[PDB]
Length: 170
Image (cartoon, rainbow, N blue to C red; front, side):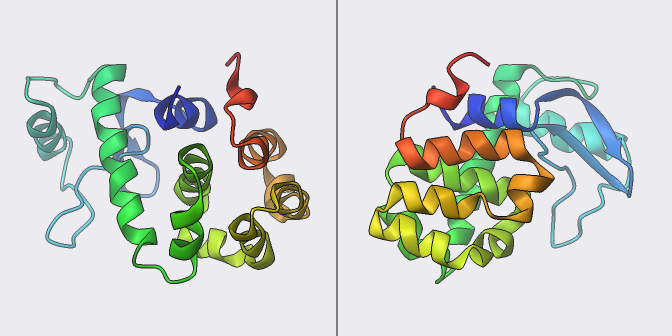
């Protein structure tokens, strides 16, 4: 399996462009549209679907497919990797983590941004030392584990086992 199925379950693949509440167009897996020349609002549905169209290469009026949504995640997935690598706190940890454990990380990043993750200081210090079990335990004494227990459990199982067990049937 991969990170894409992972996040799909952990957040969700929306197939139809929905103009966020605050002011913003998302689609697929939280892939917003409009990020450009450092200005975040698309200025409409119509540039919304065009930017979207271009990405893809077809005339979706604001509707793509799951595969379509996938060739964007991985694109955002790499995009993220690019921010961590610039981040002195996460990078050293991320370097050492094996693929599965990387995804696990990347996963918290999609959910709370590099600072949030960068806040789990010793939990981080643990995964770098490869004291899985403890990192785990440590990760669950957070508001996070509490804010969202289910998603938290999965990610932490993934971090602790480095295997994909948690998603075995979703």
